[PDB]
Length: 329
Ligand SMILES: Cc1ccc(-c2csc3ncnc(SCCC(=O)O)c23)cc1
Ligand SMILES: [Cl-]
Image 1 (cartoon, rainbow, N blue to C red):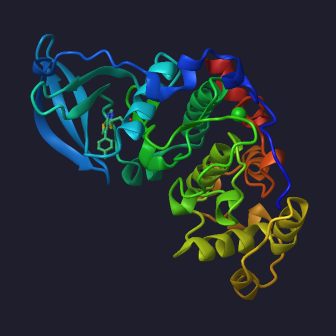
Image 2 (image 1 turned 30 degrees about the vertical axis):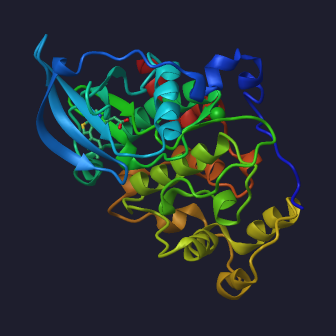
């Protein structure tokens, strides 16, 4: 069997809370009034939800309504409980209301509206300072949810809403998020392929908050090198290959060895042998204005195979890469 693992930080925050904090099945939802909201237009669709721009007709404010499709209620209750636990935290999307058809019982989450610019258009216009600023806003959200015992597990640009004119960032879609309990074996089928940490790709189930810091590193790399997504595999196996062509295969094998992970024999054929590339190799004239020694040092400390060796969100905020941001706060 593999070697056990426990989070370096916030290990027992849920152990100490009363049962009701993390026991989302027991939670009793307080429902608002469905007739306060009028749907205006469809914004998009998840695999288990559709998202609408809407208007709160009592105050004419814009809101976003996410109608959740007939799925197991346990999944819905977990997202609600997590959103309520984190409400008011820095850069965490605000759940303003929960409503349901009084006759058909179909449930809908009402969120504060963010005037988002789609990242595929926004990112290519961000300056070096913008990237540092928004990375720091995400770290605030992640340190907050991690300190409250919660892993996001789907950190990616699609789940980061940015009202750019107002320098306003919110981390959204807590539908994959989960409470951390030390020693628990979690589903590795989380996050999006390009942002999956190596622990997920090698089926190491005893992961923790540091999963989110890998995803963050992936985002950072795509922003400062202007290469989105940075690690572009065509399936989970190829995804670890793309990581290994950058981080190198030796550190990957050290990781697997350290945790006594039984690596699928298919992997050895396709992983090959790759040196670790210097982060400088990805710098060129089209991204150089976004790259600094600080940026590369910070990136290097997020994108580590060993989840235990990655910066925590709070350590990351201490990094010199953010020196000018912090004075601005
Ligand atoms: C698929 C999709 C469609 C629209 C939006 C969206 C655009 S602006 C905006 N402003 C606040 N929220 C959302 S989504 C609801 C929050 C959540 O699911 O956690 C959006 C986000 C995702
Ligand atoms: Cl953390």
